[PDB]
Amino acid sequence: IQINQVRPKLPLLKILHAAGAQGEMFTVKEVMHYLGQYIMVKQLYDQQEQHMVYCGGDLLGELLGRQSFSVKDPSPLYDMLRKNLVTLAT
Ligand SMILES: [Mg+2]
Ligand SMILES: [Mg+2]
Ligand SMILES: [Mg+2]
């Protein structure tokens, strides 16, 4: 297996699939692409303040353990990725 591949855990993979991803293993860039598409297409960001993501009530909020987060202050999102990505480079 390639060193730059990661395997998203079940609930994260569900999100990525729900945004148009195919398969089980991805680069971190691909994961971010599909996660971004999920947020963008469902329009979870506040249209009036687009760095704010209102994720509570959605699977993404469940996974994050937060009602909302800011894209400018990504640590809660990065916490979620740390816990939901299986990697070989770590
Ligand atoms: Mg794909
Ligand atoms: Mg695959
Ligand atoms: Mg961090």
Image (tube, helix red, strand yellow):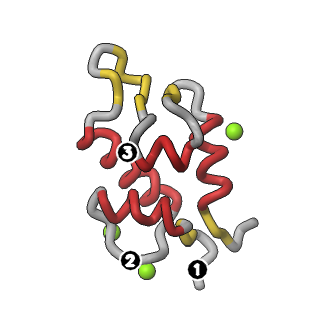
Q: Are marks 1 and 3 in contact (CB under 8 Å)?
A: no
Vertical relation: 50 (above or below) 41 = above
Tell which residue pokes out farthest to the right in this image.
Answer: 90
Frontmost of labels 1 and 3 is 3
Q: Earlier in the sequence, mark 3 or mark 2?
A: 2
Relative horizontal placement of residue 42, taking residue 3 as reference (left or right): left
Q: Which amino acid type corresponds to the residue marked 1 in the rendered image?
A: Gln
Q: Residue 23: which numbered mark, if any?
A: 2
Determine the secondary structure under disc 3: helix
Residue appearing at x 64%, y 35% in the figure: 75
Relative horizontal placement of residue 85, taking residue 33 as reference (left or right): right
Q: Quadrant of residue 82?
A: bottom right
Q: Quadrant of residue 31?
A: bottom left
Residue appearing at x 38%, y 77% in the figure: 23
Quadrant of the snapshot with the C terminus: bottom right
Residue appearing at x 36%, y 16% in the figure: 49
Q: Give the spatial CA distance, label 3 vs label 2.
A: 17 Å
Q: Residues within 10 Å of mark 3 (few under 14, many from 20)?
A: few
Residue designated by label 1: 2
